[PDB]
Amino acid sequence: MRDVVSFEQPEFSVSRGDQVARIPVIRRVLDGGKSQVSYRTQDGTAQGNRDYIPVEGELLFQPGEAWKELQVKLLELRQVRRFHVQLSNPKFGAHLGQPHSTTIIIRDP
Image (cartoon, rainbow, N blue to C red; front, side, top):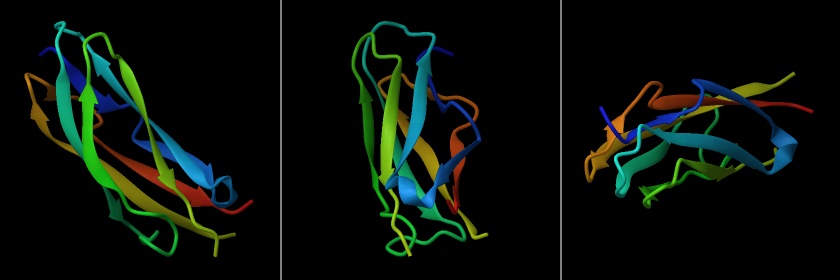
């Protein structure tokens, strides 16, 4: 498979006070053209509009682009809560690699 798009890791840890989670998405084995995938957040024990600001959209990789950083806003309130981000719907010849979903762990300062 070419143009393989994945999260870099199955888990990321962030502090609740950071204001944003910075989530890396990579594209590997470039064939030379554009790629697109969809992404979306999904609640776990962390909930949209309480713990973080939910977001969904498309990641359009132009030719040569090997990575993106998603920025999901975090909200302030030994607490630990989790939300998820999923990739779906590859287009323009793209494929999903592993891991295609990830978990963002929000911890206290």
